[PDB]
Length: 51
Image (cartoon, rainbow, N blue to C red; front, side):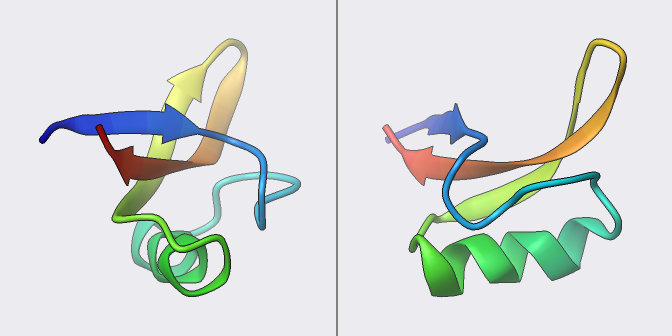
């Protein structure tokens, strides 16, 4: 198991707080993790799934 990233699901916008959208992913789209991943040109909450 590692973490695979997936931006779309519950997230749409900017990455406000790591823990916030992490939890949001896990609750909504049911990810394992989620954080501000720096994709050009700005941090977005990318949800991390177990892969």
